[PDB]
Image (cartoon, rainbow, N blue to C red):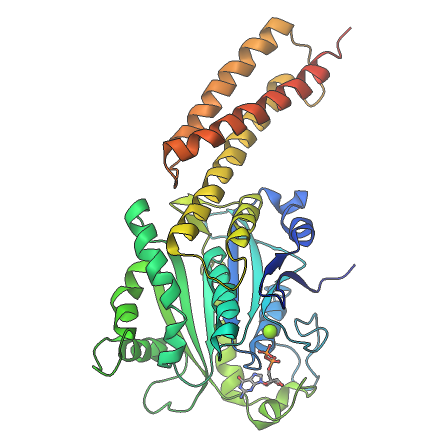
Length: 411
Ligand SMILES: Nc1nc2c(ncn2[C@@H]2O[C@H](COP(=O)(O)OP(=O)(O)O)[C@@H](O)[C@H]2O)c(=O)[nH]1
Ligand SMILES: [Mg+2]
């Protein structure tokens, strides 16, 4: 029925990660949105840090682009669809919004925006692994990762980034492109507007001090500061102020808007567009290929097989995963091209085509669609690629078959 948060990936108590593929397919494989280039916005962070709360206002904005006052009526309590849904009942894992959002970039492109909520605990390793895995995945998939910290970017906050740098540096060498898109530090209750101002301007001078290496204090947090900037195309920071005390000292805050502090609402109002304004949306791209919702479904499947058991994958294994998904996505794109181009000539209905003619069109469009497959960059390497080549040839042969059926409907 109506939209709500659907728990697509969950961490099992046995330390294994189960991905509800079916729900993922309902959402991203729907015909309306399947073929759209995709923006994947994820918020990740500790439990009980104001994530859902924020993500509300992200929905309020998405369902109300037109409004100047999407934030809502001040004398009315906050209402609308809710990420908090059933109160937690909190478990490490990833939630996505049941409704994908369709939006036009300034250049007329109709993109799909996917909202991810990433919940995990960050305290004990047997509990960090899962979190760092959920975090890994979350970041791997997302085009935009907003990292939701409480009061400051702390060393332990920067620690969870360690897992990427190893994999980044590796991916970077093999692809010759930086591996991740945008990472955003969202500092939650900033209390030094006199040291750095709230919002992006100020958030950025803050992040520059915090990320600068060689307090001499840091240890192998040096390694992260050293390489963090090479792994991410862009890294930014937003200083968000305290919601006021009615919001902080209450669970499932049911108050009216006026209850929320003014400077929190002031700044919340620039923040959300900042992240999800049409100009600000960043299309997910791996290797320099833009990714399709269908395409994105491949990367889920691939990365999930990797994080099985307590042991975490080595960059090398992750890398190989990215190769699978990257290769698969090329198949779908090339097969889509063949399929859609064939549909004109063969016809959704009409008109008649002589058997030998269908033959000659098919194999040229098959050879040429295979060429496009070869054209796209492949993570793994030709040898690794070649197994997928066959798959594409085989998937096209079965599409050919289906098209002789249709063709052979002219008496
Ligand atoms: N101190 C503080 N508390 C907040 C903020 N935003 C929300 N809260 C409150 O903190 C509690 C946890 O927020 P919640 O939405 O459940 O975040 P989540 O549990 O991480 O998804 C809720 O009762 C909120 O009412 C914030 O920016 N600062
Ligand atoms: Mg949440």
